[PDB]
Length: 143
Image (tube, rainbow, N blue to C red; front, side):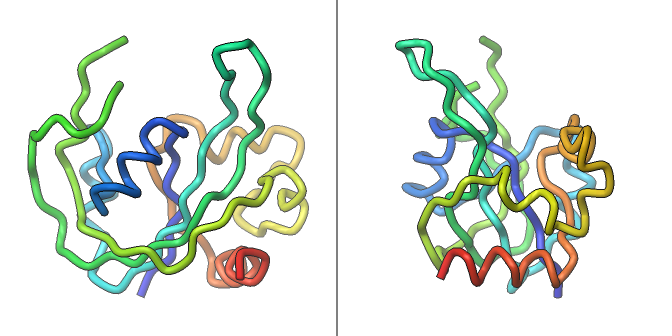
């Protein structure tokens, strides 16, 4: 098996939730090739600003299970300034849906080596493998 944390934002999270699809750009197709049916996905939305200008901190919004082998589909379901379609995809199904702030978990997450500059572990990543302990920690807090 394999646990993963997928990095997106709130607008794309809504699409993910509606279409039961996790997609990535070509540059990250390599990572997706390792994904298998049954793998677990922790959905993460990065820090953003609402229209009003208010700060929306990062947080985990759900957990899904992969149900398909990776495939390619250029359908325009997502939304980038650019025109990326995130054609490299795997079908998924929801295990649990609930939101919890991410920051408070940083100290307890094993994959985050540098607590100071944790962004480092997210930088230029679409998704990354999570150690089992980390997954369980999140699973519990999201029950």
